[PDB]
Image (cartoon, rainbow, N blue to C red):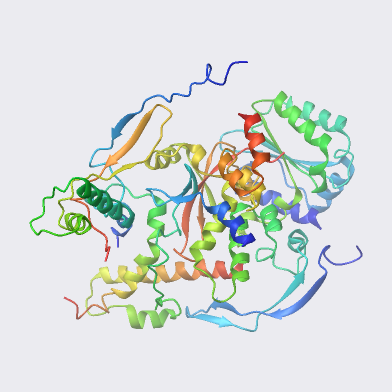
Amino acid sequence: ESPSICEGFVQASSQTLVIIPDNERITSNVLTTFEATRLVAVRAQQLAINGSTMLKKKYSSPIDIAKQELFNRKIPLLVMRCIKVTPEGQKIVEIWNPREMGIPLLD
Amino acid sequence: MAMQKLFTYIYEFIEYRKMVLLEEKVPYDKFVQMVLNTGFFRINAETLNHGIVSVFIFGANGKYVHHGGDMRTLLTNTLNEKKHYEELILIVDKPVLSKKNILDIIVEQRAANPTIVINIYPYHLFCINIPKVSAIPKHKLITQEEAQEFLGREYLQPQDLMQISASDPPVVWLGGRPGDFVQIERPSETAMHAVVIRFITKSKI
Amino acid sequence: GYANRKAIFGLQSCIVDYYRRVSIDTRLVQQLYGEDGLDARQLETVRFETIMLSDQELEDKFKYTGIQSPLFEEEFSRLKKDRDKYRQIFLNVENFN
Amino acid sequence: CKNLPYVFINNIQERLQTPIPVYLKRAASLMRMLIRIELATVKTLNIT
Amino acid sequence: TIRGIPGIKNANVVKLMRHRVDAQGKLVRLDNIYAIKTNGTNIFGAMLDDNIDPYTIVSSSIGDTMELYGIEAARQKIISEIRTVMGDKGPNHRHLLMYADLMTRTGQVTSLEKAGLNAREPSNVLLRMALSSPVQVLTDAAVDS
């Protein structure tokens, strides 16, 4: 009996974001090439949809502007890294800063 | 010639487990004839926990490895002895492990006696100094507190770690109960030896 | 193709996590990726000089005698210890192969 | 060489000198050994 | 069986190429070492025999290493077997490490077949559906909820 829904606790309990203190993070302080590439791609798409920038040197493509923002440490994004899914509905992340963190080769 | 090798390496295993003997050591001849006639050689060991561990070296084709009534009688009467009896160990021939009725009596007495742990091992576990084998890296049991510290630093529940059966020869020689952690120093062609921590699960039947 | 597809579906779920462990979902497969955590594209083959040297040859070449500080005795003992550890581990590896 | 296993964590835990897990120490053993061999005092006399 | 270790079909003397440490600490490589290589694996009988070193027994079979020695020795044997199958221009060692660590992650040697995928990832229904026999594993997932 029952249509697989009435007893179905399908709605997962909402999670609370716990941010690990800045002195407790144990992940690399250097952007992995995946993370740097994702940051550049997100920033460049957002410049395509919006167009605003903090650069002084004006470029003719959002890719170049986002790449320089990552290189010149003005990209307005925060890489958050998540390490847990606790049964207590408590997602454990540590929010890193791409401006403070090192930058891989990418070239 | 598994009898002589088993006879020397069981005592080496008792020494490896950091246990003391409650009796005097008979020689090879008395051991083998008593095994052949009685059907088992019983060895008592005392641990630092002041618990008692008994080992039963069953015969290859004796009276005790074929019929469940006698095996049941042995377990019932030996487990009511007033020793602390931390762990009981049965060392039997390899083909005996497939024989069902012995496994049934083993599990029945395990369920009947909760606090006592019973394990039945084949001969090949105690026919060689297992920790001294070249191919076997160095296993060591980390305490619960340091394992918990390692897990909490790693944000890992114990079930996340790689599993190792409690019947693994190095773990058996170490004396690893299920639910405990074993740290391993495995040689590596890449990093020149590396350390892993494995979770001990329930043994084989 | 048959073997490769079977192997791919066996291994595809192994993803390096934020600890550089290789993990399936959350269950560990490896404590560290190559047991060194290094990308396969960033490896160079270099010779370890002290491995095959005899004890007197090691003292002739690597022992520093220009200063009588015991720090250099400690440093040379560290070199000898590393050489002995390398020899032991890889002699064992040679043994079970 | 003592701080070498901290390339696996970050600079923050290097400054705070927090404990290193055993397997992290073991992972950098080969690089530590190579650095000791190649940066030995008998080989860095001319290096300021 | 009349004589010899059971399951040892053959036994041939092969000279080996091995490293030893001298009294002066030199790592000399010895070619005069002689040992035998058999056909058919029975590690237990080899440990029983006294003319053979019990602690330096090497077997090409992963199963006998798993049973006799354990899962760490089985993992090392998996690496060695995959490596000798690879040949000369083989891949990096970390890929063989990954292969061996995947199979031996559960305390038992699990295959790369559908049985091994069931053993390692039983709850990943979609992965096993993609591998092979989607209808059967779909039925099993439905009945198992």
Give the left or right position of residue E129, taking residue D7 as reference. Answer: right
| Above or below, E41 relative to B50 | below
Give the left or right position of residue B62, taking residue D34 as reference. Answer: right
Count of number-bearing discs: 0
Residue E80 at x, y = what percent?
Answer: 60, 66
| Above or below, A96 relative to B81 | below
Question: In what quadrant of the picture does the N terminus of chain E appear?
Answer: bottom right
Give the left or right position of residue E105, taking residue B32 as reference. Answer: left
Residue B186 at x, y = what percent?
Answer: 52, 58
* Residue D7 placement: quadrant: bottom left
* Residue B150 placement: quadrant: top left
- Front-lying residue, B96 or A33: A33
User: Do we see residue B203 in this rendering?
Assistant: no
- Front-lying residue, C74 or B82: C74
| Above or below, B130 relative to B50 | below
Residue B89 at x, y = what percent?
Answer: 71, 39
Residue at screen point 63% across, 69% down: E85
Residue at screen point 47% across, 80% down: E24
Which residue ends up furthest to the left in the rendered image? A56
Residue at screen point 72% across, 23% down: B112
- Front-lying residue, E116 or D26: E116
User: Do we see residue B49 in this rendering?
Assistant: yes
| Above or below, B125 relative to C64 | above
Residue at screen point 52% across, 16% down: A6
- Front-lying residue, B189 or B133: B189
Question: In what quadrant of the picture does the C terminus of chain E appear?
Answer: top right
Give the left or right position of residue E95, taking residue D28 as reference. Answer: right
